Image: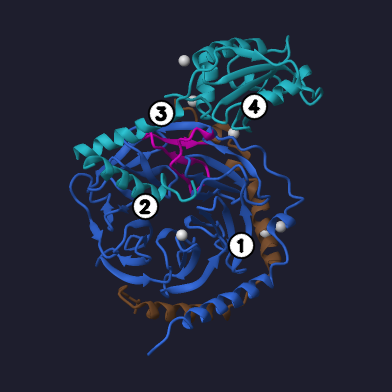
Chain colours: A blue, B brown, C cyan
Amino acid sequence: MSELDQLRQEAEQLKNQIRDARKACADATLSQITNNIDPVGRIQMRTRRTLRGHLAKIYAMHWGTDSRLLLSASQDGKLIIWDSYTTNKVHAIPLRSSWVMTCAYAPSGNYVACGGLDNICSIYNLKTREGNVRVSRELAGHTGYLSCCRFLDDNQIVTSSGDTTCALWDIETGQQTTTFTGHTGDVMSLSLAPDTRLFVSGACDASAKLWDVREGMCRQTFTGHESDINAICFFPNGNAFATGSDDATCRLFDLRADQELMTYSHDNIICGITSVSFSKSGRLLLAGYDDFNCNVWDALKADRAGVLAGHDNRVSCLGVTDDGMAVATGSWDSFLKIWN
Amino acid sequence: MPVINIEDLTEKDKLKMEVDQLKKEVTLERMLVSKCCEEFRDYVEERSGEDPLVKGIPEDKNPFKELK
Amino acid sequence: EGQATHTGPKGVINDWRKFKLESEDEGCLRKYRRQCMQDMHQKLSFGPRYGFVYELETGEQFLETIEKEQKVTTIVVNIYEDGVRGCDALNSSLECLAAEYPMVKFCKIRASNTGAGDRFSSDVLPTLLVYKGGELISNFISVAEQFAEDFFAADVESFLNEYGLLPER
Ligand SMILES: [Gd]
Ligand SMILES: [Gd]
Ligand SMILES: [Gd]
Ligand SMILES: [Gd]
Ligand SMILES: [Gd]
Ligand SMILES: [Gd]
């Protein structure tokens, strides 16, 4: 007969070894070094635009690289490409499922994707103009819901799934070029490193994994959260990233240190974090909680710098422009807002 | 030659792969958190002064100015 | 709360589930969409306890009102001083607002009565502080500057609404 119980122990002893290797470089926390840095002024953003058009809860949104066009997926089975400057609608795409979990905007603006409980990642060409009937490509493969997706370019897109996997597809052939396996739980979110050579992912096994796109395998596995990681976002310079989880805490992980540099939390905060985003300089870390509230964190000092949307329990998702000029919020009442 | 892989492996096939990855990760050379923090503080502090959401935007230089 | 169930993928999953418990327990889709949004105003719409701008006379009073208040109630406190421009207009506006948003508690107090003299110079007056759930949600120094010399309740409202500080629809 063969054996497993023992094989379950070499895993723990190895994890145990990695813990020590880490604990060996943990001489200080980030807040220590930033103790003399001046805290930021109270951050108070104001609504400049209100996007009207959806007929239901907004599930997810994503800014276009021009910091003007933005896409929004709703429970109304619609996908809307807006022009935030004028609040005008540019495209409107009927979906087959109301259960859209994510939507993405190709950096070129030529495409836009989305997917959800349909276990499929649908791609739409905005240039050939598939607004009414057409659907460029339907990426089938995952055996679990599609949690998130991010374009690498026009013929390459990465997806995360409830099937414990992440995949790199070739839009043209529509084949699952690479398959990133390793998580032991449902992958909830993913974030492309700025150079798109690497990308990180959060899952329900409480770990964040750094993957090499071009090489197709896991480089490192981060841990600290005792609960599911629901959101992950890369830091501006590519050397770190943030995570939000059900343990009501945000964590800053540095890639070179292979461990968390700081944690963001307060005793009054008891809901899970399902959304995280950095400001342009990375000084601010915006967090969306499951109670529809949003807190603005001072990435350096680890203290709340402010509240986004005055805790009106109306924030279901958010996003920051590449130019760091504005933040967008989705809501359960069907409206999106832009804040400066 | 990208790697394609279906998920109908056995628990053992996954455990194997797990210890393998874990070993690779163990051979990883790490940097002192201190050195990492200094660079984080450095990058952010010198850029936060130009961050639109940190300092605020002069009304004329705001793309989302009161529409007229 | 613990595990998420209203936002992100978790939200879609739980929305889909609660959906089924209703259709058998396109047309059923739209009904559900309306029910979720509807299901929210009601929980966010609380009883209209007030209707007037209350005057606080000491710092102890200030501290007492935000402390003992229900965590769901939004408290708008106005720190002012007579004679100082803008104050009167703001107080007028607040009286009308307090009457329209009975679920929002509106208060006013002289900078002198705060228990922090110099800290509040006419230069930053009037200052509008807004609390909720025991924590400070907004702090508007020189609020009067956010409006035209002559401003009325509807202006202060538009303003507060754009920071997401006022309830109901
Ligand atoms: Gd501001
Ligand atoms: Gd406005
Ligand atoms: Gd879990
Ligand atoms: Gd420097
Ligand atoms: Gd530097
Ligand atoms: Gd009104």
x%, y% of residue A295?
Answer: 56, 42
Q: CA distance from mark 2 to mark 1?
A: 28 Å
Residue A260: assigned label: 1
Q: Is residue A329 magenta?
A: yes
**Distance CA(mark 3)–CA(mark 2):** 30 Å
Secondary structure type for disc 4? loop
Q: Amino acid at mark 2?
A: Ala
Q: Nearer the viewer, mark 3 or mark 4?
A: 4
Label 1 – label 3 distance at C-alpha: 39 Å
What is the crowding at mark 3: few (fewer than 14 residues within 10 Å), some, or many (at least 20)? some
Q: Which x, y percent locates residue A188?
A: 42, 57
Q: Which residue is mark 2?
A: A104
Location of residue B21 with respect to C37 vertically, above or below:
below
**What amino acid type should be assigned to the residue bearing mark 1?**
Glu
> Which label belongs to residue C41?
3
Tell me, yes or no, whether the two marked residues, 2 and 4, touch with CB atoms within 8 Å: no
Residue C68 got which mark?
A: 4
Query: Is disc 3 in contact with disc 2, using a CB cutoff of under 8 Å?
Result: no
Magenta span of residues: A311-340
Local secondary structure at mark 2: strand
Residue type at numbered disc 4: Lys
Are the residues under badges 3 and 4 in a single subunit?
yes
